Image (cartoon, rainbow, N blue to C red; front, side):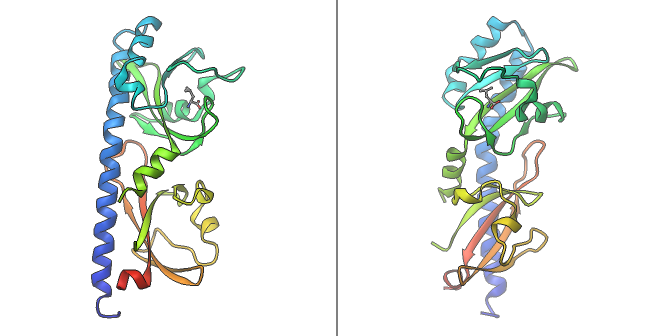
Length: 232
Ligand SMILES: CC(C)C[C@H](N)C(=O)O
């Protein structure tokens, strides 16, 4: 094994890059739809126009919901949903995220005010010549992200922030845990090209690949493979 080790490294690196590239491409189109909705909203922000934009099938078929929230606390959501009493878009993570960035952004997983399930959102400020008229967002379910990741018997991919927080993992118990909390006995390190760590009495090899071309966030694909199966 100390002969083909540099070999295995090359396969694992290649698989990480491919997986990162797929997820980037999958997210990019969705990012573009939300940006386009924001650009269009900024053309005419009257609520009738906004509603009509947000009701179109390209958006409603791609996102669980798409919406605009503004600095007065008003919001429009399509498809319409009953929101909790007192719902204020200004305090929600999609809104504060977009307001803190010069470009589009993606949230970490959070609890959806609409459905009560764990989601991420894509969001961007809708600007008319330098002035923001509000924040436009769209929601994607965790289950959707988990399925996108498990699509492509050595091992599996997961998504982790560059702060070391697991964002999306096929084991749902590890969602939104730090690497340390998720792997307490022997912790993989994003600062290492490869981490050999024992899980349930087996050696796994873990590497991390940056996902290029996302706006505002720096996230990695983690790959974890059984060390015997990989060598075999
Ligand atoms: C705007 C709404 C559809 C809900 C949004 N995802 C939230 O939790 O704030």
